[PDB]
Image (cartoon, rainbow, N blue to C red; front, side):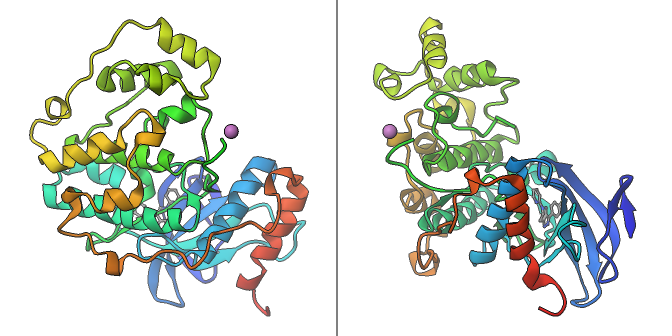
Length: 338
Ligand SMILES: Fc1ccc(-c2[nH]nc3c2CN(c2ccccn2)CC3)cc1
Ligand code: NI
């Protein structure tokens, strides 16, 4: 087995010629040569078994990505783990290798309005599918948006993905309702993140680069202005609400002042996605039908999921040893002699 950044990547003999791509909370990503398909692939090594929360994330991502089938959503082509449950310490998820991500592209490249439009379209096309299956991503950011050599875009990293239930509920792309209204299962949280990504594509810099929770709220309020009484007359964390009420008045900054060169239709859609109140924020289908996306909007070519996604078990209640058995079972079909 090859060693990448001092750590073991036990993916041979099929996968070789490893090269580091990145790491984070998702684990470590390498590219490798697949000697069967005769192409380079992406391999993600995860070590989640010591924590129940990491076990839940691993299982959710495997189940969702193996069910989903959409051009703007990354799939899972293969999964490597040990022959026995006692020996299984790591899981390797094998996926299509892309050319870059939007984080790397935004650090080196200025995008034309046609490419901002096209990328925003593909993000929403993928999000329409996810939301149609009653699922929300919850962690949309530029490093989770993959691009190939021909500008085809794929959303990845479904570790924090959950089945939506809206009726009752860095940090740079996090909706205010996550930090205030204790919401984590409303599709609107993904729209806010897409709004943050759109703003970043327009200027090559994060719109709300908060260093911490309070600083994040100050950045949002610095553009949107003070929340209205209605924006605050909802379910909100007492500490958060008292903090907001203790602050001096902040004026709203018009979108054209922050992005003076942006297409006015792009700013109009940006205004609708970056709305403080989640109940007043534009939804995915309405965002696809906005005049900014007219050149690419094609409802006859925007697949939706066959049925809502559902977990057969209460994953949050299961001890990590039980989750490990379900992961072992879910990954059995990728092993020899199945
Ligand atoms: F410059 C790059 C070139 C290729 C990729 C790529 N291609 N295919 C994948 C990835 C990254 N990736 C990720 C990234 C963050 C979280 C989970 N998974 C796994 C799937 C990324 C950057
Ligand atoms: Ni409720």
